[PDB]
Image (cartoon, rainbow, N blue to C red; front, side):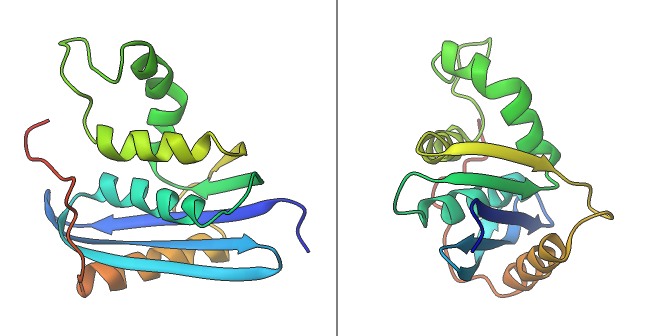
Length: 155
């Protein structure tokens, strides 16, 4: 068995907003789980956040996790935004709530249960697991069955 949980994510959506989906692969206790759902009206970025939320929330105890994703949005948030957002109570400089605050807070909550390591892969230089997530995400976008109830046009 792997001594470190493994998660791989991608999200897909054309249209801002539009029908969108996500794929996520979770290696956890000898099992490999695959998550995927499509949403009727959403954004690419909200789908990349959702992928990670769903796969992390699958974890039922404290873990060491390696998260592999090619999202620039997730990468910026993690490496540039979240720390300064927290200090300002999840507001931008103009004192408004940050975009996708609902999903960022939910992701943050999940991140805070685990020892976390990030692998920022490129899209064309992805692993078999990342490619399969891309496939799942586009297939989910094609067949949406959920509501992205947190999505707002005005941020």
